[PDB]
Image (cartoon, coloured by chain):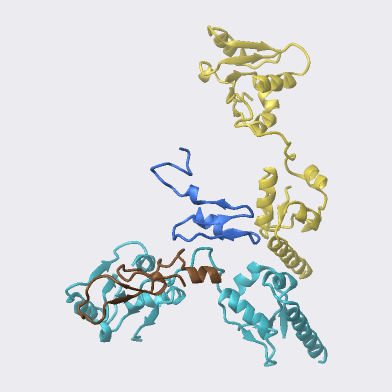
Chain colours: A cyan, B brown, C blue, D yellow
């Protein structure tokens, strides 16, 4: 299930495409926070799928201080809390021997600050979508099984459309009204 | 574990290979869709191990 | 209903599963309350008003 | 079960009529507090049926601070407490970077301050009262099945009484002593 689409559409929907695990092949035409210790970052990455960096005495930076509430929420062990507060004491001593720390302690604050949205409660299928690749290259026009069109234009889209319409058995979809991105996402969901 | 892994159904194009292999009792005669297949179906060994 | 009964919980709940690959083949709770009756069957009308 | 009554009676008993869910049709003749977050307001509205507004950085106002005791009493989750105290910290910072907050922590204080009285423990019927409408209009005199009279008077009540007494089969009730409102409420309860 391989689809061809205008380049601006994939450019605008790259985030959703990455979130739904479809690989992107496109041709162009012309401060973060860190966790005190690696264990908490690993736990939060496992829970939410969000990559988190680790503080390594680099520069005056902004530190995230996970609080007792989220410590209990994430199921963190006693040793993790102990090492977190040990690193906290080390930071206290370092800044007393003359960096900003935030004690985030609500789940919504952490979500609205950084990271990916939590997981919905449905059965997990083998794959999120039935499509593997959406591309905008003439080099793999024979690779495609269907294509999508929009009133928006690309300098190479006309030739690709001509070379794709020549296929004997290919599915063709066109969008005329509403939002192009919403229609494309609905199609990629139902295809 | 208590599964029929090998069976013979009809003569094959090659007469020397009549066996049909089926892991976990899954039949190869039916096509599947990756999005929804496998939800709520188990075999004996997996259920016992769980 | 299957999703509601299995996937919703504020705390751990005991659950048992059945062999067949159909919705509502499970037994939930401390007591063995089979949920097979709640699967729709027009020939007998179990699990609904009739 | 439709009733006709003098306008002053319904004017004086509008609160009770609204509380008992009978719709009012009448013709005339001539600072609040807010909750830190929407979740607590929604919970208290569900528990007591009292509408509560939400603080939105409007003006110097009066804030209600639900305390640990009522937090446990209302069955509020950990995340609700966390977000409440996060908003509290935000308010501390806002007023330190130069609004009144009250830490109500007894159930009776909250009831006597604002809101509706708690619920009684009886079986819940399908409907509170058997009557739907009490009105004071000649436009729906044929709508009524019974009427109530009192020594009090309205400029339109005499004509309505004459037009209602002409009905062949209508129930008539009159109050002579005691309190008019109490008699009317007892009648609407027993009718």
Q: Give the quadrant of residue A79.
A: bottom right
Q: Residue A26 location, x and y as percent? A: 35, 83
Q: Is residue A5 visible?
A: no
User: Who's the residue at 24% across and 82% down the image?
Assistant: B16
Q: Image check: A15 left or right of A90?
A: left
Q: Image check: C24 left or right of D183?
A: left
Of residues D9 and D3, the one drawn nearer to the viewer in this rendering: D3
Number of numbered tags placed on the structure image: 0
Q: Give the quadrant of residue A134.
A: bottom left
Which quarter shows the C terminus of chain B? bottom right
Whether A43 is drawn above or below A120: the answer is below
Of residues A185 and D29, the one drawn nearer to the viewer in this rendering: A185
Q: Residue D173 location, x and y as percent? A: 66, 12
Q: Is residue B15 visible?
A: yes
Q: Residue A19 location, x and y as percent? A: 46, 74
Q: Residue A61 location, x and y as percent? A: 68, 86
Whether A122 is drawn above or below D5: the answer is below
Q: Give the quadrant of residue D90.
A: bottom right
User: Who's the residue at 64% across and 59% down the image?
Assistant: C10
User: Who's the residue at 48% across and 38% down the image?
Assistant: C49
User: Who's the residue at 35% across and 62% down the image?
Assistant: A178
Q: Image check: A166 left or right of A80?
A: left
Q: Image check: C45 left or right of A117?
A: left
Of residues D181 and C3, the one drawn nearer to the viewer in this rendering: C3
Whether A119 is drawn above or below D41: the answer is below
């Amino acid at each position: 299930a391989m689809l061809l689409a205008p380049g601006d559409v994939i450019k605008r929907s790259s985030e959703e495409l990455k979130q739904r695990q479809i690989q992107i092949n496109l041709i162009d035409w012309t401060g973060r926070w860190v966790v005190l210790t690696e264990e908490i970052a690993r736990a939060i990455e496992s829970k939410y799928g969000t990559k988190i960096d680790v503080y390594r005495d680099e520069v005056p930076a902004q530190i995230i201080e996970v609080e007792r509430s989220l410590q209990k929420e994430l199921g963190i062990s006693r040793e993790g809390v102990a090492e977190q507060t040990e690193r906290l004491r080390d930071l206290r001593r370092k800044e007393k021997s003359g960096i900003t720390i935030e004690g985030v302690m609500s789940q919504k604050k952490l979500l609205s600050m950084i990271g990916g949205v939590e997981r919905k409660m449905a059965p997990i299928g083998a794959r999120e979508s039935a499509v593997m690749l959406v591309s905008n290259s003439i080099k793999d026009v024979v690779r495609a099984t269907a294509y999508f069109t929009a009133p928006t234009g690309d300098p190479h889209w006309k030739e690709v459309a001509r070379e794709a319409s020549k296929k004997k058995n290919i599915l063709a979809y066109t969008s005329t009204g509403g939002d192009v991105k919403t229609e494309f996402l609905h199609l990629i969901d139902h295809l | 574990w208590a599964t029929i892994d090998v069976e013979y159904r009809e003569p094959a194009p090659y007469v020397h290979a009549q066996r049909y292999i089926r892991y976990c009792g899954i039949d190869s005669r039916e096509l599947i869709n990756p999005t929804t297949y496998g939800i709520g179906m188990t075999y004996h060994c997996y259920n016992e191990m769980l | 209903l299957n999703d509601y009964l299995l996937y919703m919980y504020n705390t751990r709940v005991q659950v048992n599963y059945g062999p067949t690959g159909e919705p509502l083949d499970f037994q939930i709770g401390r007591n063995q309350y089979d949920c097979n009756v709640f699967r729709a069957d027009f020939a007998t009308g179990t699990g609904y008003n009739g």
